[PDB]
Length: 60
Image 1: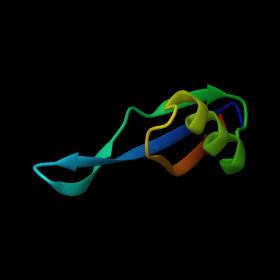
Image 2: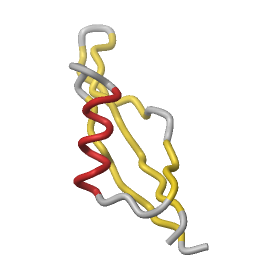
Image 3: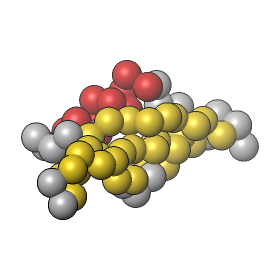
């Protein structure tokens, strides 16, 4: 496992309706657990309603 892609989404208010917007994926070196990824994304998008969708480790 040499890298981990974290896929992230945001709940957004558009024309008065709650929708979900895809945010840029971020690929980290090494293995990142889902707990680690959730923590990292909560610090990155301070105060905004973001949620980790998935993590994808790649072996090589």
